[PDB]
Image (cartoon, coloured by chain):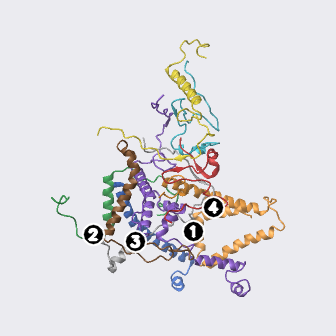
Chain colours: A green, B brown, C blue, D orange, E red, F purple, H yellow, I cyan
């Protein structure tokens, strides 16, 4: 009752390990929670045979 | 002076700069009270733009 | 280096093929690293949007 | 300058995938030094044709400025085809990223 | 010595001193009133509005 | 030729009016620092407000708006490499929040454009039967006399 | 009545303003040394930052 | 042409009456405000008079109206 | 026999039947959505906006 917590488990005592899959999961969850129509929209793309000009 | 009793939003628009300065001074005082410092890196190769230029030393 | 290259790619067309494959492999690995960093930046941008 | 039509025709042949297979077959038993020397010799042959034939011959495009006008027109054509196109693309990029004039904006006031 | 510098461009062909574009928020027209009607003439490319 | 010029008179390294002198002067200014890139402590003096920098950022971030990352790079360059505990003034804070708002609007409304956010693009989506009407007259506000 | 708006201002490029992009710019791509640096630090057991500790 | 040469006592319908009053209003506005232009009257011209330092700002966002749910 | 006629223009070079400009009040874009972005291409002369 002294701490602003729902439970006693404050998470792991070591940081997460780097993973493409975990990053994908977190980004998808954030996108779903935000629910913003306009993410990933490209109004202008440099005209090129390459799909992604520059990066 | 800005008559915040009658135009509080208008006065806050004028006074938030001094609130921000107070906010800065608070941390500036805390870091002097509790000795807080950081490891500065070595001097850059092009710290001076020109060799003949003076490098005025800053604390 | 020129010996090792000409021993395995004595002709111009083979030299060009090897050069192009080197370029493609370099670009692919660079794309992998850029994709990882891009995922990180996307997450940071999403947290800015959440703010 | 001369043989502009032939240069267009050469580019047209070069862009043909059949000519790519022909060049692939022609590249059998061939060296980069040989290819470079061949191209350099071709370019030298062009400029030598110019240097020789300008002494006695005049093309249909001959004018009181000589080949200076032909070279200026070549430059302007290259400019209008490539660089102004790139400027258009860069303009749309900057306008989508920052707004019109975003690259000449003043620094943020302190 | 802590204030930032404005970009400098000067040549025979173009410059950035005959006008002021402003900040990111408080923008303004680089050209003046007499040549604003002829802005199309100070451009290599122009993509007009849709209406 | 350059070597012999060095021992010829009035033809030493960068002295004189010869092409060897010009080339040596060019190498000298290259070897100097003035044309080197700036350090991270000095990036927000010119580089982060540069048209080249902005265009390159926009190019290598194709469909994105790097105004916010530019603001954050300025914050970094002033805080972590120059030693300022309070890098942003009130103006810069307002600019940061303006850019945050613009990012928010661009991700919320698809295709939003100039009058609401600083952004212009040509290939737009229109309904198909576009009606054109006159704006209403400005609202008559009450006034004395 | 805000989404999918029409082009309100013109887009243009002033004469002889520079572009700073070459002809291979579309094939150019970025890179950061941070991932490689992280891998190397993890493999060589170098000093970790305190952000690894919750 | 409808009244005096075809014999119609009531030449204008409601649409034509509205159009007449719209054009009357446009004449009034054009004569009242110098340089008035498209959004208020159907009219576009190029040689306009501008202040000299024209500032460009973003419009405010459309007013949030209250709504159910 | 008491309604008025709309104007007719038809030739090999130009016409007024591929679009509708509307009335004096209830106007509309004569060109359709796919070519509205390219209005500059359907004009012999173009005098852009002031901004």
Residue G51 placed where, x, y %?
A: 30, 69
Q: Which of these two is toward me, D88 or F20? A: F20
Same chain, marks 4 and 2?
no
Q: Mark 4 lies on which chain?
A: E
Q: F93 left or right of F133?
A: left
| Mark 1 element type | helix
Q: Given this view, does label 3 or label 1 mark the residue nearer the observer?
A: 3
Residue D19 placed where, x, y %?
A: 60, 66
Same chain, marks 3 and 2?
no
Q: Given this view, does label 1 or label 2 mark the residue nearer the observer?
A: 2
- F90 vs I19: above or below: below
| Mark 3 element type | helix
- H40 vs I40: above or below: above
Same chain, marks 3 and 1?
no
Q: Mark 2 lies on which chain?
A: A
Badge 3: residue crowd in 10 Å (few <14, some 14–19, many ≥20): few
Reading the image, the residue beneath label 2 is: A15
Distance of label 1 from label 2 (alpha carbons): 56 Å
Q: Do the residues labelled 3 and 1 touch (CB within 8 Å)?
A: no
Distance of label 4 from label 3 (alpha carbons): 38 Å
Q: Which of these two is toward me, H47 or F127? A: H47
Reading the image, the residue beneath label 1 is: D21
Quadrant hosting residue I41? top right
Distance of label 4 from label 2 (alpha carbons): 53 Å
Same chain, marks 1 and 2?
no
The residue most toward the front is B1
Q: Which of these two is toward me, F56 or H65? A: H65
Residue F136 placed where, x, y %?
A: 48, 33
Reading the image, the residue beneath label 3 is: G34
Q: Given this view, does label 4 or label 3 mark the residue nearer the observer?
A: 4
Reading the image, the residue beneath label 4 is: E10
């Amino acid at each position: 009752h002294l701490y602003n917590v729902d439970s006693t488990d404050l998470g792991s005592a070591v940081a997460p390990v780097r993973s493409k899959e975990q990053l994908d999961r977190v980004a998808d969850s954030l996108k779903a929670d935000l629910n913003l129509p306009g993410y990933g929209h490209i109004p202008y793309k440099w005209e090129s045979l390459r799909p992604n000009p520059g990066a | 002076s800005a008559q915040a009793r009658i135009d509080p939003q208008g006065a806050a628009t004028k006074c938030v700069k001094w609130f921000n300065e107070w906010r800065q001074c608070a941390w500036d005082q805390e870091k002097m009270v509790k000795g807080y410092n950081y490891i500065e890196d070595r001097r850059a190769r092009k710290h001076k733009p020109y060799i003949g230029a003076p490098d005025l030393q800053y604390s | 280096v020129n010996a090792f290259v000409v021993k395995h790619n004595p002709d111009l067309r083979l030299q060009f093929v090897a050069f192009a494959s080197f370029i493609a492999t370099h670009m692919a690995i660079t794309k992998e690293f850029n994709d990882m960093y891009q995922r990180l930046v996307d997450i940071t941008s999403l947290l800015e949007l959440q703010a | 300058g001369f043989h502009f039509q032939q240069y267009i025709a050469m580019a047209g042949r070069a862009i043909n995938p059949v000519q790519w297979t022909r060049a692939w077959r022609r590249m059998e038993g061939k060296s980069a030094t040989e290819v470079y020397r061949d191209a350099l010799a071709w370019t030298n042959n062009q400029f030598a044709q110019i240097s020789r034939a300008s002494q006695y011959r005049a093309w249909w495009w001959q004018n009181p400025l000589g080949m200076g006008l032909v070279l200026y027109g070549t430059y302007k054509a290259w400019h209008m085809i490539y660089m102004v196109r790139k400027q258009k693309k860069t303009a749309q990029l900057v306008a989508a990223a920052y707004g019109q004039g975003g690259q000449w904006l003043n620094p943020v006031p302190r | 010595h802590e204030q930032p510098y404005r970009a400098f461009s000067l040549g025979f062909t173009a410059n950035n001193l005959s006008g002021n574009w402003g900040d990111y928020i408080d923008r303004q027209d680089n050209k003046n009133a007499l040549m604003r009607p002829a802005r199309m003439m100070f451009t290599d490319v122009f993509i007009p509005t849709t209406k | 030729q350059f070597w012999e010029a060095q021992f010829a008179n009035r033809s030493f390294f960068f002295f004189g009016n010869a092409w060897t002198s010009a080339a040596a002067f060019a190498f000298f200014i290259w070897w100097s620092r003035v044309f080197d890139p700036p350090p991270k402590e000095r990036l927000d003096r010119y580089w982060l407000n540069s048209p080249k920098f902005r265009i390159l950022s926009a190019f290598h971030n194709p469909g994105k708006r790097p105004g916010l990352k530019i603001s954050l790079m300025t914050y970094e360059a002033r805080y972590c490499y120059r030693g300022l505990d309070h890098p942003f003034t009130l103006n810069e804070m307002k600019d940061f929040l303006f850019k945050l708002r613009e990012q928010y609007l661009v991700n919320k409304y698809e295709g939003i454009q100039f009058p609401f956010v600083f952004r212009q693009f040509n290939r737009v989506s229109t309904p198909g039967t576009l009606e054109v009407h006159t704006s209403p007259a400005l609202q008559q506000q009450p006034h004395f006399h | 009545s805000m989404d999918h708006g029409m082009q309100y201002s013109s887009i243009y490029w002033e004469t002889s303003h520079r572009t700073y992009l070459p002809f291979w710019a579309s094939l150019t791509q970025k890179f950061s040394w941070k991932i490689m640096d992280d891998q190397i630090r993890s493999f060589l057991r170098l000093p970790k930052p305190v952000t690894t500790e919750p």
